[PDB]
Amino acid sequence: PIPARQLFIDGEWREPIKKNRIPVINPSTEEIIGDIPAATAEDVEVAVVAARRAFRRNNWSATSGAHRATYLRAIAAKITEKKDHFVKLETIDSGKPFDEAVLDIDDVASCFEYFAGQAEALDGKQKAPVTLPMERFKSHVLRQPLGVVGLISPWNYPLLMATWKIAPALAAGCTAVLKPSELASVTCLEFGEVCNEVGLPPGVLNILTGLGPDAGAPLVSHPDVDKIAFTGSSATGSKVMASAAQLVKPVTLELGGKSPIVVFEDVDIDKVVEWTIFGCFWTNGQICSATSRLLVHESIAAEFVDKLVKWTKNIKISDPFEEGCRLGPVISKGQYDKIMKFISTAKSEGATILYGGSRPEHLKKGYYIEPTIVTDISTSMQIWKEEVFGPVLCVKTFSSEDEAIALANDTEYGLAAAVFSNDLERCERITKALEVGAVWVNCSQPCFVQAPWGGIKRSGFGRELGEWGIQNYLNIKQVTQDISDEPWGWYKS
Amino acid sequence: PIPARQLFIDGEWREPIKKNRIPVINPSTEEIIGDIPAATAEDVEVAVVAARRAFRRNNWSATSGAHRATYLRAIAAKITEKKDHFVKLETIDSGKPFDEAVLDIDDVASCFEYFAGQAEALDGKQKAPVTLPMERFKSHVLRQPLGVVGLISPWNYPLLMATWKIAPALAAGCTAVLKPSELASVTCLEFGEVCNEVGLPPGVLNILTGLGPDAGAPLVSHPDVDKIAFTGSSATGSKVMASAAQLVKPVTLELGGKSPIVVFEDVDIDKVVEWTIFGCFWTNGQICSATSRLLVHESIAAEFVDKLVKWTKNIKISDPFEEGCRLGPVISKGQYDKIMKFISTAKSEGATILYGGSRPEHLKKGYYIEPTIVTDISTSMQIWKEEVFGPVLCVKTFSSEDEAIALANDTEYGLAAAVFSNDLERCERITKALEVGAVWVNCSQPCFVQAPWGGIKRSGFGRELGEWGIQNYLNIKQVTQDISDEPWGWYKS
Ligand SMILES: *[C@H](O)C[N+](C)(C)C
Ligand SMILES: *[C@H](O)C[N+](C)(C)C
Ligand SMILES: [K+]
Ligand SMILES: [K+]
């Protein structure tokens, strides 16, 4: 029983103006389980217009952070109260294991709770004094919402990624149009009803589902959208920013990557191996910050890889709703094909499939893929360079720190990295040298809402979460006042 | 007495690779008084390589901010020492009255001193801890230089606008390539000598003078440049960001505007009139933040208007070196033509040229334009919409406060605005309502390095100066560490 909704615009359920709709496919069974509306430019026009009027009213954007925080905590509470519903809907549609989805939904609650406090902190930052060296002038800073924002979220954490954008935008006092991925939109549409139950003012959040080209692209190009927040592939990020440039519209981008996990010899191998599979295979490999390039010190390489491979065999590939399930199907046929082609090309280029590379034997149907390990890698192969976004790991060995650092930085990406070593002095050295936005030490993949997140290089720019997240949605307004009533005395009179 | 320089690359003076030069014109005489090296894509390539090299060395980017602050203070002292040299050069190059150039070169020194302060305080921000909920993980933030940056600065405050970008970039630990405007590059080139004399490591700052498409565009699209800071026209900002989009590289943009000065009945007219003059006619009207749209209350419009022209007539237009000069030529023939066309077009549209609109008849050579006041304006007119960048003021009346805000916000731009009223509670209302990044209360145009500066809407995005400027050049790196030494316990062995 998959919900059936319209678009969420101005607090109402509205059918797309041209009434089109697209299927919702369960990645486990490969067959349609329902539908979602497919918006077009006409609908964006309506949603943005609704966003702008909600911005202009006297019950949201000009109110205090403390006021909006009540709605943010209500949202978190309404999410928690309905966690069972959301977890299940996230588990079908997206395809990640049930145990992954429960942690997702718990995190969207924590995220709204965290940004509620941040909204509250915002008030305490209004009219912050700025010291001037002329007693004639006083100065302070106001922090006001930019206006109407376009939020474009990816399908690997459907509600949670949307939350990372929605929560700071609302905290800041902006109003928003959210466009989730057509691959996994059901929980995001459900969120629309959470907004009504908490009495979020009509138009403050608008949710348009649909194809990127049909719904997303006009959101980005709309002349009354003040800012875009995009999470996605680097390729699409170039397009979004190019589009935003024609109206010189600001943009924050987090664009995935090819992140390295560097493993030195002085490690407890069994623990590090468990992080290594968590860094590449969790979320079915579909992790923007996946540590897909394992760089392991030559001396423990043989032992590491062997411990690695049957840790990998003990991971249970099943239907998402099955107990103990630790790997679901990848999100779509399209993704399925691409990941299998990456595997095929890897071999054709002369790499070895040390393990996997095929559909699991005990799962005839569904876009399932065994956790794949690739060795015999030269840095020239496409599998070393390109983002696979599937449960495939690449292994290479290295001599020393210099080779490790060089190999780890040998990508045009720069999102994250993980370094593993009992020498903490060495851990600090590598962290400083890694050309990335986030470094895990003796772990891989924990993302707390408390701390700043974002990449550099082809992984994008801007920082979300932590005390940076709300700043992306703010107009920093300088206010400078002449308090002397003396003439300026520059001209003559 | 005007220097003949080469490009400043890797600490030494280099002939452009294809060896071109372009003239330096005194805007006051229309005389060619010298020439400047004209760099091309080949020279950009050499400068970027030199900057990358200098970034990888151990004497700059990974040193402390305390260490880099000694250089910034040496630069401030060198500038103050050579104050007379730089002021004379800025005056003859840019056309601005000598007394204005005096304030500009003082401010340059002030900017390097303030950011010396910012560099120092960067050290106390390193490894700032971030409290996590789970005792297993610890977190902190590192603030590291982004890498090699491209700085593209305008001609209206030549050395000062460059400093606004150079000072924080060096503070952050970046290496930079600066491309000043070809209409006014002399002092920026002379800055290369300041760098050698304080011993800045070679390649840390590189100065490429030359034409926009030849030197600027290659810098923007260069694959080893990690970020661009641009100030200039909105039309060019769009093309800059579009180019940056290709490689998804971050930009900051400050793109001028059409800023309103709003004047209510409860004011001292002689004092507000002087600020109105300063906000539109100072820097020969070449102010990115010029308050070029006078909105004056109906009840006092008549008086205000001709007290305005009284003051205006008293403005000494002359050669900038002449004692008492309060208005010099605009920068170039091109700008002179465009400004005249703006005036020509306004009267064809039916506006009144109340005063000025012509070349001053006591000055037969030089790009001199009379301060111009245009009344009988419809908001449909070009001169109400488009940035003139000349000494040209637009005047419109209003009845209500609602109408004033409406008119003030009736623009695609949003850089600055100024509000005049002795009623301060009313001043506070208006400041909150104005869709701009900078509001002046009972004054017009004072920019202190202590306060953040930038616009919204088509005036761009990002904040320079104050405690914001250095952050545009940092990689905010999250570092999170598992300190538990226990299995993750997610995957079964
Ligand atoms: C944490 O690893 C970041 N994501 C978005 C991947 C959860
Ligand atoms: C302050 O007025 C800003 N400018 C750039 C004009 C000096
Ligand atoms: K789906
Ligand atoms: K000049």
Image (cartoon, coloured by chain):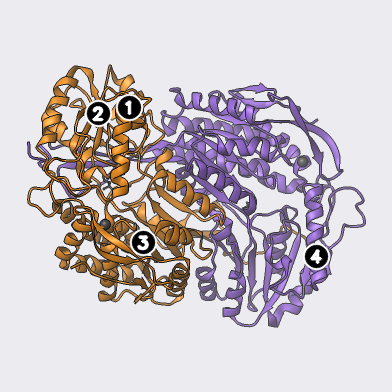
Chain colours: A orange, B purple
Marks 3 and 4 sit apart, C-alpha to C-alpha, by 47 Å
Residue B185 placement (x, y as % from top left)? 70, 37
* A359 relative position to B41: left or right: left
Name the residue carrying label 1: A348
Q: Nearer the viewer, mark 2 or mark 1?
A: 1
Which quarter of the image is occupied by the C terminus of chain B? top left
Q: Nearer the viewer, mark 4 or mark 2?
A: 2
Is label 1 in contact with label 3 (beta carbons under 8 Å)? no
Is label 3 in contact with label 4 (beta carbons under 8 Å)? no
Marks 1 and 3 sit apart, C-alpha to C-alpha, by 55 Å
Q: Are marks 4 and 1 on the same chain?
A: no
Q: Crowding at label 1, few (<14), some or many (≥20) Cα neighbours within 10 Å?
A: few
Q: Are marks 2 and 3 on the same chain?
A: yes
Q: Nearer the viewer, mark 3 or mark 4?
A: 4
Q: Amino acid at mark 1?
A: Ser
Q: Is mark 3 within 8 Å of ligand 1?
A: no
Q: Amino acid at mark 2?
A: Val
Q: Amino acid at mark 3?
A: Leu
Q: Nearer the viewer, mark 1 or mark 3?
A: 1
Q: Which mark is residue A122?
A: 3
Q: Quadrant of residue A182?
A: bottom left
Residue B278, above or below B401? above
Residue occupying image coordinates x 80% and y 63%: B343
Which quarter of the image is occupied by the N terminus of chain B? top right
Q: Which mark is residue A374?
A: 2
Q: Quadrant of residue B65?
A: top left
